[PDB]
Amino acid sequence: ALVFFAEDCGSNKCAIIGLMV
Amino acid sequence: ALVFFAEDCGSNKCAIIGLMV
Amino acid sequence: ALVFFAEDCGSNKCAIIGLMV
Image 1: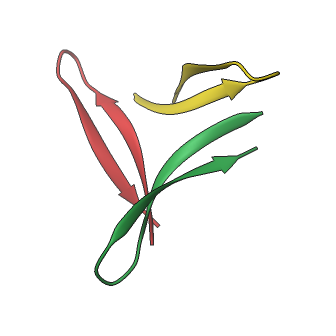
Image 2: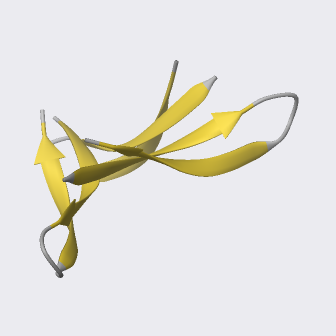
């Protein structure tokens, strides 16, 4: 599968997450 | 929001950008 | 063009690939 990269950002706090397809 | 990352490339050069959703 | 990035995962190997738009 492919894993794209995003940051999940909220109230001045970001965390990297994968989005798997 | 989610922030994805892309290299935005012109003829000679590339910059990293966030694409925010 | 924009180049996005993904980890392409097979049975064992994982490599980062670009994806161009």
